[PDB]
Every structure is written in C-alpha cells, then in structure tokens.
Image (cartoon, rainbow, N blue to C red; front, side, top):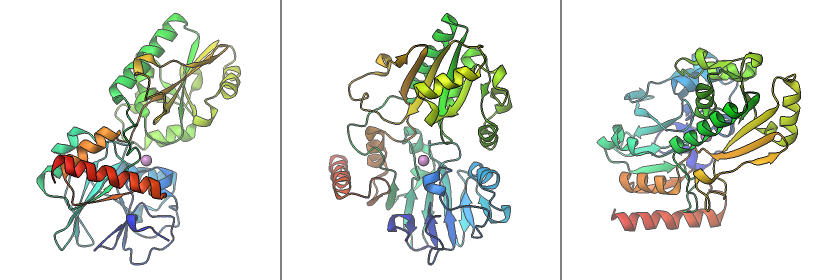
Length: 341
Ligand code: NI
C-alpha cells in the first residue's frame, strides 16, 4: 500500500506512486523523473492521467509505450491548473527531465516536493522566491555530514584532463564509461568532445538519449562503435573481466582501456581530494571511480532548507529505519535553531 510520504494532502494527487496498483482517491499521478525506483509500475496498460515534464513524457511514450492520450507534459516555470489546483514544475538539477513540484492548495497551504534533486543557489531565484512554503517533501539521500563531494565542474575537469592525457600518450587506448540509467551524460559527452570523437553505444541506449532534447546530440553520439574511441557500456560490465572481454571484441584496434565509473559517494571522499584520485589497475586496464553526484551534499541540502524556512519537513529517502529517521530529525532541528525560524 502507498506510503503517506507519496500522498499530497487536500488533493487527489500522488507523487512517484505507480507500484501500488490503483491508489484509493487518486485522480492524477505525478512522475518527477524517469528513474526505475520512481516509475516502477508504468506500462502501455496504464490508463490514468500522468503529469510530468516534456522529456519525461518522451521517455514514457518511447521506452515504456505509455499511450499518448494519458501523458500530460507541462512546461517548466509556468503556472498550470490540474484538476482545479495550481501547480508549477521547476528544474531539479538531477537527470534530464527531472522536476520539483510546487502545489498551491485551495486552503492556502503551499507544498514543495523536491523529487530527487541536487540543491543549488540558483534555485533561490526561481518562482520559489515569491511565496512562503509550508511543507517540504525532501530528497534526504545524503542527509549526514560525512557526505561531502566536489562540484560537478571539478569532477568533469578531472575526467577530461585524465582522458586527454592518456589518449595523447597512447593513440591506441580506448575510453569506456559505465551507465545504467539516464543522468550523468556530461561525463561521457565531455570526454568525447576533448578527444574529437562521438560516443558509441547500443541501439537501446542511443534511443534513450534521442528522447532527451539535448542540443546537437546527433553531433555527439552514434551506434557505430568502430568509428568511436569513447564507448558506453552497462555499469555491471565495468570490471576487469568485462573490460578484457570488450577489448577482445575490438579486433586489435586498441591495446589499453581507461574506464570511468561515475559513482554517487564513496568513503574515499572523507580523506581524499579529487586531485588525489587514483585508479585500480590490472595489466592494460585502469578503472577510475569518480564522485559525480546528482543529489545534494549535506551542506548543499542544509543551505537550501535554511533559505526556504519550511514549517514542516517530510523526508522521502532513508525513511525505513528508526536510527535514520532519528538522525535526520535531529539535523532538521539543528538547522532550524541555527537559522532562527
Ligand atoms: Ni533519481
């Protein structure tokens, strides 16, 4: 049965709640982004209205075959009316097509559901600045002070410089990047751009990427692996066995692999600067785990919430254990006392 933290009070609405069957009293289903923990349950047989971004709606139609008549895409940064309630979709700084949802309840309560997000000061100048928010349904993935990670810009600088150095030293090296969902496209796109190559991938992944409105994408990606020196592979194949096997397939075109696994956080973060990251190496194969996050660090999360000053916070992540829940509630109280709201 649907958990309370997926239900919007005073409306007929749910958020990311497609795996519970027909939810009692739900007249419209919102989907914040196309990640499987969130869309789980959607298919061509769904016949309720789904509200989402344009990009999410392209993925619903093309990848899951949801029928067009039930997809209701909304423009960003635009007041819209849904079953008599005003809503606004905002950029969540997560994967492509990911949104936060502002609901303006008929009784005057204003609710922000962040979906999955990476808080940024740029959000302090969206339509959020213009009214008070009473309740915040918060992506608390990394709600603990041990979770520090560098900016996305620093991580991409490291990756570009590392790849460009390796291939310049050895023109016969192949670069491989791991993927298992949408998100983190900058990793593989930036490396292909510095090397003057397209990124080669499976037809299924190319299809996925063509749904994302990324400008000049026909310019950066391809299904012709033979013409490409940056390859995308399933995240599960980014290990020494899976990579030795791939190198065999390239028919002696290459004699070395440099591979990247964009992880979220890994405890090498608490001790080591991005400058200082080193690969695991075996033979002619090296693997770098790089901390490219699409969720808030602790400090980014803290700043957003202390700026927004909500009256009540509802966590959406790490809610299944009493120790997690207790930890998060103690941080929310600190933040409120330190800021004075
Ligand atoms: Ni997500």
